[PDB]
Amino acid sequence: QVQLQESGPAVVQPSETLSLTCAVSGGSISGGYGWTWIRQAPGKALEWIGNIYGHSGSTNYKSSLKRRLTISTDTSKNQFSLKLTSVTAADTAVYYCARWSTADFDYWGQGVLVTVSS
Amino acid sequence: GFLGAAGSTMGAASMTLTVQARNLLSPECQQHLLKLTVWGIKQLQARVLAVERYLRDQQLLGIWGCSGKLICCTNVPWNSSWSNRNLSEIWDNMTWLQWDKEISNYTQIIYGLLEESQNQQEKNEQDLL
Amino acid sequence: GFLGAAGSTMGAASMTLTVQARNLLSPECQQHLLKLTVWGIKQLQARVLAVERYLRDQQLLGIWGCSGKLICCTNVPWNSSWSNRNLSEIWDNMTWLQWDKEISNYTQIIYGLLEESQNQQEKNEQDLL
Amino acid sequence: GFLGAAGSTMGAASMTLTVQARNLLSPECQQHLLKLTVWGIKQLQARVLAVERYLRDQQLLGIWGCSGKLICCTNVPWNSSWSNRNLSEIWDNMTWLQWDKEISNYTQIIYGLLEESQNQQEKNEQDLL
Amino acid sequence: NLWVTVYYGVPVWKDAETTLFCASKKHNVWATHCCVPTDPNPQEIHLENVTEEFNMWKNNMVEQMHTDIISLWDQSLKPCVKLTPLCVTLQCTNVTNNITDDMRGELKNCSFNMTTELRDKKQKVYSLFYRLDVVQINEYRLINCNTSAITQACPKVSFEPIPIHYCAPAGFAILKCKDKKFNGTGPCPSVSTVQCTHGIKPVVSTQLLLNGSLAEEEVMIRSENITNNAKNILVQFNTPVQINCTRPNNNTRKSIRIGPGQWFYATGDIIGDIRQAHCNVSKATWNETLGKVVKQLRKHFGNNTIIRFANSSGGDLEVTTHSFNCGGEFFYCNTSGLFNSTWISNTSDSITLPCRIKQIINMWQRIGQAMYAPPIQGVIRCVSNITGLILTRDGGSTNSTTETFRPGGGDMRDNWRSELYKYKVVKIEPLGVAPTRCKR
Amino acid sequence: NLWVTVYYGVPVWKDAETTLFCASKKHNVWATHCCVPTDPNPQEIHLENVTEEFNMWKNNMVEQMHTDIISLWDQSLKPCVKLTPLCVTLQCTNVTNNITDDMRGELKNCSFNMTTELRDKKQKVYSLFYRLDVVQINEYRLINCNTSAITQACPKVSFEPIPIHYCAPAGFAILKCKDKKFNGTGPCPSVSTVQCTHGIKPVVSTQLLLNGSLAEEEVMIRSENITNNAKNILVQFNTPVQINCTRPNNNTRKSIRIGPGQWFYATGDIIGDIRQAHCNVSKATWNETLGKVVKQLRKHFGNNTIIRFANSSGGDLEVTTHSFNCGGEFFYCNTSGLFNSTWISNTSDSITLPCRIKQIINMWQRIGQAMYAPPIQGVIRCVSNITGLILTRDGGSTNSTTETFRPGGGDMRDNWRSELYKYKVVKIEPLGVAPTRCKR
Ligand SMILES: *[C@@H]1O[C@H](CO)[C@@H](O[C@@H]2O[C@H](CO)[C@@H](O[C@@H]3O[C@H](CO[C@H]4O[C@H](CO)[C@@H](O)[C@H](O)[C@@H]4O)[C@@H](O)[C@H](O[C@H]4O[C@H](CO)[C@@H](O)[C@H](O)[C@@H]4O[C@H]4O[C@H](CO)[C@@H](O)[C@H](O)[C@@H]4O)[C@@H]3O)[C@H](O)[C@H]2NC(C)=O)[C@H](O)[C@H]1NC(C)=O
Ligand SMILES: *[C@@H]1O[C@H](CO)[C@@H](O[C@@H]2O[C@H](CO)[C@@H](O[C@@H]3O[C@H](CO[C@H]4O[C@H](CO)[C@@H](O)[C@H](O)[C@@H]4O)[C@@H](O)[C@H](O[C@H]4O[C@H](CO)[C@@H](O)[C@H](O)[C@@H]4O[C@H]4O[C@H](CO)[C@@H](O)[C@H](O)[C@@H]4O)[C@@H]3O)[C@H](O)[C@H]2NC(C)=O)[C@H](O)[C@H]1NC(C)=O
Ligand SMILES: *[C@@H]1O[C@H](CO)[C@@H](O[C@@H]2O[C@H](CO)[C@@H](O[C@@H]3O[C@H](CO)[C@@H](O)[C@H](O)[C@@H]3O)[C@H](O)[C@H]2NC(C)=O)[C@H](O)[C@H]1NC(C)=O
Ligand SMILES: *[C@@H]1O[C@H](CO)[C@@H](O[C@@H]2O[C@H](CO)[C@@H](O[C@@H]3O[C@H](CO)[C@@H](O)[C@H](O)[C@@H]3O)[C@H](O)[C@H]2NC(C)=O)[C@H](O)[C@H]1NC(C)=O
Ligand SMILES: *[C@@H]1O[C@H](CO)[C@@H](O[C@@H]2O[C@H](CO)[C@@H](O)[C@H](O)[C@H]2NC(C)=O)[C@H](O)[C@H]1NC(C)=O
Ligand SMILES: *[C@@H]1O[C@H](CO)[C@@H](O[C@@H]2O[C@H](CO)[C@@H](O)[C@H](O)[C@H]2NC(C)=O)[C@H](O)[C@H]1NC(C)=O
Ligand SMILES: *[C@@H]1O[C@H](CO)[C@@H](O[C@@H]2O[C@H](CO)[C@@H](O)[C@H](O)[C@H]2NC(C)=O)[C@H](O)[C@H]1NC(C)=O
Ligand SMILES: *[C@@H]1O[C@H](CO)[C@@H](O[C@@H]2O[C@H](CO)[C@@H](O)[C@H](O)[C@H]2NC(C)=O)[C@H](O)[C@H]1NC(C)=O
Ligand SMILES: *[C@@H]1O[C@H](CO)[C@@H](O[C@@H]2O[C@H](CO)[C@@H](O)[C@H](O)[C@H]2NC(C)=O)[C@H](O)[C@H]1NC(C)=O
Ligand SMILES: *[C@@H]1O[C@H](CO)[C@@H](O[C@@H]2O[C@H](CO)[C@@H](O)[C@H](O)[C@H]2NC(C)=O)[C@H](O)[C@H]1NC(C)=O
Ligand SMILES: *[C@@H]1O[C@H](CO)[C@@H](O[C@@H]2O[C@H](CO)[C@@H](O)[C@H](O)[C@H]2NC(C)=O)[C@H](O)[C@H]1NC(C)=O
Ligand SMILES: *[C@@H]1O[C@H](CO)[C@@H](O[C@@H]2O[C@H](CO)[C@@H](O)[C@H](O)[C@H]2NC(C)=O)[C@H](O)[C@H]1NC(C)=O
Ligand SMILES: *[C@@H]1O[C@H](CO)[C@@H](O[C@@H]2O[C@H](CO)[C@@H](O)[C@H](O)[C@H]2NC(C)=O)[C@H](O)[C@H]1NC(C)=O
Ligand SMILES: *[C@@H]1O[C@H](CO)[C@@H](O)[C@H](O)[C@H]1NC(C)=O
Ligand SMILES: *[C@@H]1O[C@H](CO)[C@@H](O)[C@H](O)[C@H]1NC(C)=O
Ligand SMILES: *[C@@H]1O[C@H](CO)[C@@H](O)[C@H](O)[C@H]1NC(C)=O
Ligand SMILES: *[C@@H]1O[C@H](CO)[C@@H](O)[C@H](O)[C@H]1NC(C)=O
Ligand SMILES: *[C@@H]1O[C@H](CO)[C@@H](O)[C@H](O)[C@H]1NC(C)=O
Ligand SMILES: *[C@@H]1O[C@H](CO)[C@@H](O)[C@H](O)[C@H]1NC(C)=O
Ligand SMILES: *[C@@H]1O[C@H](CO)[C@@H](O)[C@H](O)[C@H]1NC(C)=O
Ligand SMILES: *[C@@H]1O[C@H](CO)[C@@H](O)[C@H](O)[C@H]1NC(C)=O
Ligand SMILES: *[C@@H]1O[C@H](CO)[C@@H](O)[C@H](O)[C@H]1NC(C)=O
Ligand SMILES: *[C@@H]1O[C@H](CO)[C@@H](O)[C@H](O)[C@H]1NC(C)=O
Ligand SMILES: *[C@@H]1O[C@H](CO)[C@@H](O)[C@H](O)[C@H]1NC(C)=O
């Protein structure tokens, strides 16, 4: 049904801003779902970044990223996106977008492997 | 615990002023009074009147410079015409009920004098600075 | 005996503050108002409102440290922008009605400053002890 | 601007007492409440009750000698049974909500003692003169 | 040099919108309405200077009277009979016996089937009626049946217009304007403070104001806007005009039990001749009075224009006639005989006004309600003081030819502002500040 | 070392039981009920920490609304017509003209002898009626005659559910819980103080909650006790479901004078075809919505149990149907078409709900009273937001087989606590003591 698909830079340099867009098809961006960013650092377990609701904003961010991280949507393209400023080496991960519903993530994208490197 | 001092001499009863002064502001009815509201009117009138009386006493103490404390000296000489009596004849031998009767007709004389004593005192302080 | 000072200069009228302040709390109807009780409502509303106004004035004097007496100095410098006038120009030549108009738009400025002057004064006393 | 201090330590919150105290006395309905007057009764009851509560607080401060100012020392020793705590443990670390709970069951003990402290103080002044 | 110093008890004020007390027979509604005594009222405090601004056309004391008088009236008559059952088909003929010609067709004699106290029996009763209360079917019905069940005013409720005084509540004061010939607005130079106003008689009327106060010096003509023909002109006379009104015909009253404790009062047979009600106005007095009015009126009109008085054309009784209540009955008198003149702007014993009466009275416009005044036995004799007039302009194109002026009706507010123009209520504001050379 | 020191203005409080003000069309009852303005309300003060304890199931603001709304309703309609005289034997036939099959027997055409304004004449009148208001004798009578004289709601009184706000009186404050997904009880970690609540629309309904607020994030299922089948479950949706309701049939209205100022409104002949009232609920939207509800519901149920939705069996219209008022008319719609599903616990365009209407409405249980809504002319079109549901469990023995759940009725308290759960009112207690190192 719902298909999510990430896109954006594979390589971002240190200190720059990483911007990943997750297109939504097979459903609306405006629905009552938690659009969520999750990343898995290479060799590591999966880590939650934050989310936003299709009908309300009302976001949730990992607190350690709140000063660098913005999550927003664009309803004209039926998409949501992840904006992370001042990236560092520790931010290398494969970033995935997912659709949160009630108790689990019903839908997942493919992910973008992002390397932070000059 | 309330009016037991009303028979004590005025002097002895001066220690119970707190006892009497402290009582001045002392479901189901909640629904009953909102129906047949004449009862509600009577209760509101009673509450309001208690408040008005309270405030007038406070206003009198305010105007005389006696707001705060239960006993204040006002510097108005006692006129021994209002009561040509010794303190040993009244404080030690009379009760407040008797005393109130003894000088009931000077109440308004004294109160006017008390207001002026305060007016002069405030004027003097403002004139000094 | 009441508002005759409203035309006197502010200075002269300072001696009548008592005259006006003292009037603030100033059978048959007893049965009439318990019937056709809308009349009872009007009377209760009037009584209550008089009380509320009275208490708000007292609360303002309380918060500014001017509860008690009719005249108090509050240590807030007069800002000659509120009124860039001499005392001989206002106390001796203006009436209170004129004055009230002259600075009507600073009422809230002054009151906020007065509240803080008192806050600082109480703090200082508590800090001393 | 009102209750934001309710979580601050008691010490920090001592600077907002004015902020909370100042809010205590805070057409069309004019005709609506004179009809279907049960609504008028509810409004009058609310107004009256606010006044009564206000006056009882003032009466308590009056009887304890704390009428005027927001903070007063009353010379009643603190009994470290009511609360066997250090000031650095309560003023610096507890909020007023927590504190009120901590000693809620001594409210009446302290108040009775406060009334007597004042009774003794007034007696002493009258005895001196 | 100077610091804020707070002064409490400062003699200042602001315009107020408040409720006045009322202050003062057994049956009189005002007597029982406000028991608050008044008489010892040398409480008038002259204020030097001040020069307060008044505007009688915006006076909220007038508005208060309107609301309270209507309420008192309705409350007083609410618990009476409620003659709903009287609204039935009537069988009527005219009264044709000891009558004059001016009364032909004026009175009806109607019979009907009225209920009795038992809910199974009827009685045949009759009453005489005035034609103004009865409407022909296509048989007759009472006219009110079109919109309202009506009541019967209680015979034990008195509306004699005894004067009442209004008094301000604590925190408020009333400023009285003593400026002789004050027109009604602006900076009145001479004022005084009272707690209570003088007494005002709550007299209800159209066209001619009765039993009010008289001007202290000269006739006063005042209006909100003298050049606006949409506004009423109030005229206060400095001398009264005597008017003698009567209701001839010695009437009797029946008492019919229509239900278990419900009595209806019917008009019974008339004793003696049946004659028309009327009012007598002194001819010379009226002439002099209008002469004074026009001489004053001319202040606002072109030189040597010609001013006339005219018949009160309009669509109803409360519009075209002089309504009033006296002796308990409601009169509707024809004043066309008074308002008929030309003043030329260069000039060198009883006017009888025919009058009719009614029982089913709506009182204040309204659609429904109405009080059915009960009959009064015997005869009525009333003598009143005409103290003023309410008039309007035509406002047409001007080619000389000044308005021919007409007396008229309006609501009750205009019959009160004519007295209330002297008073304003203000709120006392005792707390204020000024700079002073002092510190704590 | 330390002495009692008294501090006044201390920022503390206790739970309160008080009366809130209400704050805000000409005819709307809430518009005229509370004139107290509200809009400029950035008066929300965030409180750090605090962690106040809430319990929506004990919220006395809900109780206040119940009492005040009923009172306002009754007061507003008390002074209307009081159609006692309409309770007579009716002569009826069915309406059989331009009709559909689903309306056969739905409408009656009844004639009767009505009174006229004169207490001696009758008139033959007729009105169309819905069968739900009319009961056959052994001829017909109005159904209410068994217990009550009924009134006629005034055509000039509007019950459009405009939102109102509640505000605390001085000495009290309202604590708002901002904890997203707060279930309704316990230590809400994030609160703020307001003097006034947000506006709430006083919408009356059963089964489906209309035009309320939506959940900020996800669907919330809350109940006093989730394991007690005697308790209702309130469900708040995070998205609205669009429901389009209509009453076809272009109706007209008669106006019959039944007495002296008493008018009755009858239903006249219908213009065009006579069709059944109904509501349209988006099929996909409803499906998605319940899917979200069950996914949340499962939190409290056994693994992979099977959950179903079912028909609202019960004994009355206010029990089994979706009642609401829109366009001024009272609808009773059949929701069995919505509550019919199995979720399998492993799964991968307009539902039409037939609906009937009534005029004789009791409103709040009760035995007597009832308001006879007058007819509305023309047609009715309503679009509403379904914002939530009220459901119950069966509570039977468990052998897997989870409840088949049913929507249902209840009193109005449950349609308000769904919004009021966010608010608590407390009493401010400014006076208190603490030890301090000082003496006078
Ligand atoms: C402008 O101002 C004038 C002046 O005040 C005013 O006219 C006056 O109106 C009042 C009321 O309409 C008139 O008073 C009535 O007078 C008659 C006549 O009685 C005379 O003789 C007695 C003998 O002792 C004298 O005391 C008295 O003064 C007269 O000389 C009275 O009979 C009237 O009283 C009856 O009616 C009252 C109605 O409320 C009852 O309350 C009262 O109990 C009396 O009722 C009894 O008798 C009735 C007779 O049929 C009977 O039906 C009842 O059941 C009951 O038994 C009343 O006193 C006064 O005389 C008028 N003044 C003049 C000069 O005529 C104008 O009306 C006023 N203008 C306007 C527009 O307001
Ligand atoms: C959930 O929320 C929705 C959204 O608000 C709400 O639905 C709305 O309900 C209201 C009230 O039922 C609807 O308002 C009515 O709309 C009709 C249609 O008028 C249209 O055209 C005019 C032209 O200027 C527009 O202004 C207007 O907005 C519409 O586009 C109006 O005719 C209604 O007014 C009449 O009835 C009122 C009843 O109180 C009268 O007060 C008013 O004076 C009008 O009466 C006159 O006309 C009558 C016609 O026969 C006549 O009988 C009367 O005597 C008199 O002459 C009213 O404005 C609004 O449109 C609905 N919104 C939608 C989208 O449909 C839901 O009801 C709500 N759900 C629940 C359960 O509460
Ligand atoms: C208004 O109409 C009524 C109804 O006709 C008139 O009353 C009627 O008056 C006549 C004459 O007074 C009454 O006749 C009586 O008959 C008895 C029979 O024995 C006789 O003894 C009496 O002397 C008298 O003749 C008649 O009964 C009476 N009707 C009623 C119902 O009372 C009334 O007089 C008319 N009023 C006017 C102003 O015309
Ligand atoms: C409900 O029942 C009433 C009562 O029968 C129906 O009203 C009746 O309708 C008929 C036909 O419209 C009316 O007949 C009229 O007769 C006159 C005679 O000259 C004729 O000129 C008219 O053109 C018409 O034929 C009849 O008077 C009327 N009755 C009443 C009391 O008004 C009503 O239509 C029925 N409504 C429905 C929905 O069935
Ligand atoms: C009421 O009168 C009695 C006397 O009749 C008062 O009694 C006095 O009590 C004190 C107590 O120590 C004694 O010392 C006095 O000698 C008593 N008086 C006499 C005359 O013996 C009593 O105090 C009076 N009133 C009250 C309220 O106690
Ligand atoms: C009202 O204005 C008059 C002046 O127009 C004030 O009269 C003063 O009265 C005192 C009394 O001793 C005189 O010494 C002054 O010289 C008078 N003024 C003038 C200009 O001559 C009067 O005081 C003013 N208001 C009131 C309330 O008295
Ligand atoms: C609510 O709790 C927080 C801590 O959880 C308090 O925050 C303090 O804020 C001051 C501001 O300068 C800091 O110096 C403190 O260090 C903070 N506390 C901690 C533990 O870091 C906050 O003051 C409390 N309540 C209110 C009303 O502010
Ligand atoms: C009171 O009611 C009776 C009964 O209806 C009326 O008298 C009837 O009038 C009709 C008119 O033609 C006659 O045909 C009947 O025979 C009469 N019956 C009786 C018993 O008289 C009577 O006219 C009504 N009276 C009034 C004054 O309205
Ligand atoms: C009452 O008389 C005063 C005059 O004392 C009128 O006030 C004047 O109105 C004209 C109108 O343009 C102004 O230009 C004058 O300046 C006004 N005079 C004052 C002193 O303000 C007042 O309008 C008259 N009011 C009525 C009701 O006729
Ligand atoms: C208005 O005045 C005119 C003029 O006096 C009245 O008309 C005259 O009335 C007398 C009455 O007997 C007649 O004799 C005259 O012949 C009438 N004049 C004319 C020209 O016909 C007129 O009636 C007065 N109107 C009113 C309402 O009194
Ligand atoms: C209105 O009342 C009349 C009078 O009782 C009813 O008509 C009577 O109906 C009975 C029934 O058998 C007949 O025997 C009478 O002859 C009828 N009388 C008349 C004058 O028609 C009439 O049906 C009632 N109408 C309604 C609609 O209820
Ligand atoms: C709302 O959620 C809270 C959890 O934050 C529930 O409170 C818990 O209830 C269980 C029941 O046994 C207790 O053991 C926990 O200690 C409670 N937690 C806290 C923080 O007190 C609460 O019951 C839920 N309320 C509703 C209405 O579902
Ligand atoms: C509940 O769902 C069942 C299953 O879809 C509905 O029954 C079917 O309704 C369709 C409607 O045309 C029929 O064609 C099927 O044959 C029905 N199934 C069976 C087994 O008979 C049932 O009507 C639904 N109930 C409601 C209230 O909508
Ligand atoms: C009753 O009044 C009408 C009014 O014109 C009149 O025609 C009729 O002749 C009058 N009846 C009698 C008996 O005079
Ligand atoms: C009764 O009311 C109707 C309503 O239009 C009106 O036409 C008629 O003239 C009224 N009756 C009278 C006597 O005015
Ligand atoms: C009214 O009656 C009195 C009684 O003496 C009389 O003097 C006066 O002239 C009369 N007035 C008129 C207009 O007749
Ligand atoms: C009133 O004035 C007119 C003016 O011409 C005069 O003719 C008439 O006789 C006067 N009436 C009286 C009573 O003097
Ligand atoms: C006064 O008379 C002259 C004469 O022609 C005229 O023009 C003028 O308009 C008159 N004044 C008024 C105000 O009518
Ligand atoms: C007064 O009676 C005359 C008689 O011709 C009539 O023309 C006039 O319209 C009547 N006026 C009123 C107000 O009744
Ligand atoms: C009226 O409804 C009843 C209900 O069963 C029906 O039997 C009867 O035939 C209907 N009458 C008509 C005319 O359809
Ligand atoms: C009327 O009341 C009786 C009382 O028991 C009841 O049995 C009957 O069913 C009621 N009528 C209707 C239509 O329910
Ligand atoms: C309700 O009407 C609106 C009008 O545009 C429409 O868009 C919506 O889909 C309708 N809803 C249903 C359930 O038909
Ligand atoms: C609702 O869900 C059921 C689950 O099997 C499905 O069969 C049905 O087609 C769905 N309806 C819509 C409108 O998608
Ligand atoms: C979960 O499944 C197991 C399978 O046997 C069952 O025993 C257990 O009771 C189920 N849990 C619940 C809560 O129903």
Image (spheres, coloured by chain):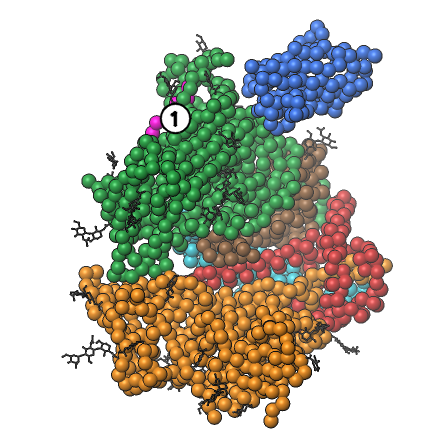
Chain colours: A blue, B cyan, C red, D brown, E orange, F green
Image x and y of residue B1, in percent:
50, 53
Instruction: Determine the residue positioned at 51% across, 70% down.
Output: E410
Q: Quadrant of ligand 3?
A: bottom left
Q: Is residue F71 at all visible to an observer of this figure?
A: no
The three-letter amino acid code for the residue at tag 1 is: Ser
Is disc 1 placed on a helix, strand or loop?
A: loop
Image x and y of residue E93, in percent:
26, 75
Task: Say whether residue F309 is magenta.
Answer: yes
Instruction: Determine the residue positioned at 44% across, 26% down.
Output: F351
Q: Is mark 1 within 8 Å of ligand 13?
A: yes
Instruction: Determine the residue positioned at 19% across, 40% down.
Output: F138
User: Which quadrant: the C terminus of chain C?
Assistant: top right
Depth order, front residue of E317/A28: E317
Q: Is residue E134 left or right of residue F21?
A: left
Residue E312, relative to residue B55: is it above or below?
Answer: below
Give the magenta part as a residue range: F308-314
- Residue F404, located in which quarter of the rendered image? top left
